[PDB]
Amino acid sequence: IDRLITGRLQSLQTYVTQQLIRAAEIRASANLAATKMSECVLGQSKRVDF
Amino acid sequence: STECSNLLLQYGSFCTQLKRALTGIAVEQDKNTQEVFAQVKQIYKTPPIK
Image (tube, rainbow over the protein chains, first blue to last red):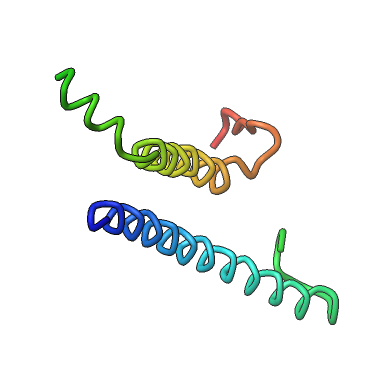
């Protein structure tokens, strides 16, 4: 039972770490989307290819 | 080693996960190189007179 507990804890910690990295990437994309909504929908943009 | 490989098969899909993450890292670097330099549609040429 100790061996199985150690294996399942390692697997679940790996899942949590990968979820944290994906959440950071998704938050960066959401910040970019919020900036695009604030600058291009609510006004006219002078930035090239933004 | 056959015995170590058969003992490694008793573990989970860890080495499928670590192989899948590094492939996603390696594919991402080509996207990084493509996003920066390949912004121009046609390969322009300069005139001979400079």
